[PDB]
Image (spheres, helix red, strand yellow):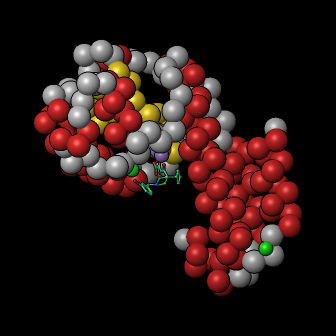
Amino acid sequence: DPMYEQFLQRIQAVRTATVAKDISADILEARHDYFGRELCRALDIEYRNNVLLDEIILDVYPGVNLMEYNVPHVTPDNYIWTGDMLLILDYKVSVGHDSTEVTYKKYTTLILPVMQEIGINTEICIIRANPVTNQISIVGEQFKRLFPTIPVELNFARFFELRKMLLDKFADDEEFLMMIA
Ligand SMILES: COC(=O)/C(O)=C/C(=O)C1(Cc2ccc(Cl)cc2)CCN(Cc2cccc(Br)c2)CC1
Ligand SMILES: [Cl-]
Ligand SMILES: [Cl-]
Ligand SMILES: [Mn+2]
Ligand SMILES: [Mn+2]
């Protein structure tokens, strides 16, 4: 697993809180992308990770004149264009709901208004994995309808192992315990 080994090498060598903070953030981003790949694989949908909203619009509505609209340049993780409906997808890996709420608010208020002007029926979907319990929580009524079961096989233990080693290595470093938390 060259992903695990790459983090381990960085954790072995890191000496400063700033480089350590970046490793921690990279591990959190990596387990996020791991969940997205596994989810898209299980649902046999196309795997994407951050698509510019303008690019989504051009895929679903090639004839659009971009310059006719105020398109926020957000990059949701992924999308599903059924031909009648656009599900905007964002992955989350978290034990809590705050990150979901924050992103739900953002994409609801920024994406829906312009998609209604353009005329594309859209739903904001956030799929969260709890990295401790592996349970999946979905917001998006149309998504649940399309995918009533999510047969993922998730294992977040290696991400926990790596990040724990990093936190252990900097447990007596005041600068670090500030930056991560
Ligand atoms: C899970 O939901 C998200 O948090 C998410 O997918 C965030 C992202 O994709 C960014 C990379 C990332 C960081 C931490 C984790 Cl754990 C997972 C992914 C990349 C995009 N930025 C938002 C942004 C930044 C600059 C310009 C624009 Br426009 C938009 C946030 C982090
Ligand atoms: Cl360093
Ligand atoms: Cl964004
Ligand atoms: Mn993203
Ligand atoms: Mn995401």
Outermost residue toward the bottom? 174
Q: Position of residue 133 (x, y in %)?
A: 56, 40
Question: In the displayed image of the protein, which residue is found farthest to the left?
Answer: 117
Please tell me whether residue 131 is drawn above or below residue 17 in the rendered image. above
Residue at 57 percent across and 22 percent down: it is: 41
Q: Quadrant of the N terminus?
A: top right
Give above or below for 139 relative to 163: above
| Image location (x, y in percent) of residue 156 | 65, 41
Residue lying at 75% horizontally and 68% vertically, measured from the top left: 168
Q: Is residue 137 left or right of residue 68?
A: right
> Which residue corresponds to the image point at 26% horizontal and 39% vertical from the top-left?
66
Position of 102 with respect to 153 (left or right) is left
- Can residue 90 be seen here? The reply is no
Above or below residue 138? Residue 3 is below
- Viewer-nearest residue: 44 or 175: 44
Which one is nearer the viewer's eye here, 8 or 113?
Answer: 113
Left or right of residue 5: residue 34: left
Residue 42 pos. (x, y %): 55, 20
In this rendering, position of residue 20 left or right of residue 181: right
Tell me: residue 70, above or below residue 43: below
